[PDB]
Image (cartoon, rainbow, N blue to C red):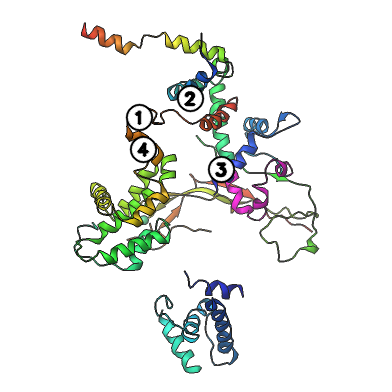
């Protein structure tokens, strides 16, 4: 199932400790104050704690990552309400940031195998092109039906607009004053 | 070799398998050898090959081998080159009710048993939807008792799904479709086997109901909660500081 | 005087007591009184047991003086 995995992952958040001190718990608590909506993670810390996520995240990273995103959102909601009760509406998904030092693999030794898996490597940087934007949450109205709807995109910054809500094909206009977007850039390496 | 076996062992969905794979391999070889059999999308080039492979070796079974326009064309070309209850007196087939039972993902033995029940007792009918619906609902309640017990939400969801699949807004008729079939199917040995297998016995265990009905007070009515429940619940407030 | 630990364990599993605990959890972000009273120190638990045992169950008395 997926919920067994999501629980085995959420336990890693608050029930993990080293050097007799919480790390990710208070890291999240500080991050929410910073208004960061992100974190940092070390995948070496996850091998010893639990092996039910490593061997399956290795081969199905795209399948497993959004679950971790939603779990982080849940933890954030709980801690947000509890902190509001402690002292002193819109909480989007939190980006997951991780690193590693297991190994490095050069571009020369790549092949057409282990495609869609996770890999490590080194290189040098060249390009800083442009802040090209993508959409995350944008609203829609039908031009004839005046029928409002909504759409949200998650990770691929798969599906297109609806082909039919007579109005005919292409019945939707795209709003901007009530939409949401993020940034990305096309980076090179050699 | 992978796709060939994928399609060949798709027939279920001793010598049969081996001879069929050999026949498919050599038949595809013959069809692709000459320049006479072209414009043939591999998308579907392992279906009537399998049909004629079944035809060849020893025995052939018409049903569920062709299971369309170009199917006959390729056959000839190769063989030359070589609400729902008000409706009255409805009709049904094997696969229609197999589909209706398979929308739940229930096993095949239960579906076959329902089909046998239908083909044995479908002569004096008024509406087969009622009997089949009751049968599948009382199969779901008997097999899914564990998850229903651990989540009393299922009851409403399942009933809504089987009320929307038959296109009705009233549900007391569905309740009748359940209780009447329970009355009718109450005394058959295969039903007995299913009962002993999935241990519903009206949704409660045998070893508890005997003492519940015998006239004792040691009967375990679980208003209290199990120790493991408390043990696993403690963790929720263990981390209450956050 | 014979309020035993096993009795404490089994009475802790009371669902209305669970409702009380969770209501207080939501009412107060700090969690000092719950750790003061809960099973983690059974003295407070038994003190609470006696405190809410001496109550009158006012429904019965209400019925009585309603008849009156
Ligand atoms: Zn429209």
- Please determine if labels 1 and 4 lie on a single subunit: yes
Q: Which residue is mark 1?
A: B216
Between B135 and A47, the one lying in front of the other is B135
B185 lies left or right of B217: left
Q: CA distance from mark 1 to mark 4?
A: 9 Å
How many numbered marks appear? 4
Residue at 68%, 35% in the rendered image: A16
Along the horizontal axis of the image, is A75 left or right of B66?
Answer: right
| Disc 3 element | helix
Q: Chain of mark 4?
A: B
Which residue is disc 2 drawn over?
Answer: C13
Q: Which residue is mark 4?
A: B210
Is B34 displayed left or right of B151 in the figure? right
Counting from the top left corner in percent of width and height, residue C3 is at 51, 13
Q: Chain of mark 3?
A: A
Callout 1 environment at 10 Å: few (<14), some (14 to 19), or many (20+)? few
Are labels 3 and 2 on one chain? no
Residue C24 on image: x %, y %: 49, 20
Is A16 located above or below residue A138 in the figure?
above
On whether ligand 1 comes within 8 Å of the CB at mark 1, the answer is no
């Amino acid at each position: 199932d997926n919920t067994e995995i999501i629980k085995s992952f959420k336990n890693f958040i608050l029930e993990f400790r080293l050097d007799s001190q919480f790390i990710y718990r208070d890291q999240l608590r500080n991050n929410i104050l910073v208004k960061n909506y992100s974190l940092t993670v070390n995948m070496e810390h996850l091998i010893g704690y639990n092996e039910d996520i490593y061997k399956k995240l290795s081969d199905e990273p795209s399948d497993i990552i959004p679950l971790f995103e939603t779990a982080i959102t849940q933890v954030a909601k709980r801690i947000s309400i509890l902190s509001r009760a402690q002292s002193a509406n819109s909480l989007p998904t939190f980006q997951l940031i991780l690193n590693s030092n297991a190994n490095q693999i050069p571009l020369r030794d790549l092949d057409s195998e282990h495609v869609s898996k996770i890999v490590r490597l080194s290189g040098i940087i060249i390009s800083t092109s442009v802040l090209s934007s993508r959409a995350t949450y944008l609203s829609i109205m039908c031009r004839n039906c005046r029928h409002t709807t909504s759409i949200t995109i998650n990770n691929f910054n798969t599906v297109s607009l609806p082909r039919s809500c007579n109005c005919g094909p292409d019945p939707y206009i795209i709003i901007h004053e009530s939409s949401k977007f993020i940034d990305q850039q096309f980076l090179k390496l050699q | 070799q992978h796709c060939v076996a994928e399609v060949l062992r798709l027939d279920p969905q001793s010598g049969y398998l081996k001879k069929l794979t050999n026949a498919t391999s050599i038949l595809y070889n013959t069809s692709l050898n000459k320049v006479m059999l072209k414009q043939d999308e591999e998308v579907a080039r392992c279906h009537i090959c399998a049909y004629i492979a079944s035809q060849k070796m020893n025995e052939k079974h018409m049903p569920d081998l062709c299971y369309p326009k170009k199917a006959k064309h390729l056959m000839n070309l190769f063989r030359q080159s070589l609400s729902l209850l008000v409706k009255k007196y409805c009709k049904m087939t094997t696969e229609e009710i197999i589909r209706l039972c398979n929308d739940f993902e229930l096993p095949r033995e239960v579906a076959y048993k329902i089909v046998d029940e239908y083909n044995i007792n479908a002569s004096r009918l008024v509406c087969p939807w009622q009997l089949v619906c009751g049968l599948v609902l009382n199969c779901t309640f008997i097999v899914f008792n564990e998850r229903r017990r651990k989540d009393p939400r299922i009851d409403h969801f399942i009933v809504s799904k089987m009320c929307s699949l038959m296109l009705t807004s009233k549900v007391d008729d569905v309740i009748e479709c359940v209780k009447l079939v329970k009355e009718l199917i109450i005394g058959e040995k295969w039903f007995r086997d299913l009962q002993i297998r999935y241990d519903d016995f009206d949704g409660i265990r045998y070893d508890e109901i005997i003492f519940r009905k015998l006239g004792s007070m040691l009967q375990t009515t679980n208003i209290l909660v199990t120790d493991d429940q408390y043990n696993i619940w403690k963790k929720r407030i263990e981390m209450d500081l956050a | 005087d014979f309020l035993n630990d096993d009795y404490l364990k089994i009475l802790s599993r009371c669902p209305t007591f669970m409702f009380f605990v969770e209501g207080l959890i939501k009412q107060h972000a700090p969690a000092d009184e719950i750790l003061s009273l809960l099973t983690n120190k059974n003295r407070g638990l038994e003190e609470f047991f006696v405190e809410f045992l001496v109550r009158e169950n006012p429904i019965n008395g209400h019925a009585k003086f309603v008849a009156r």
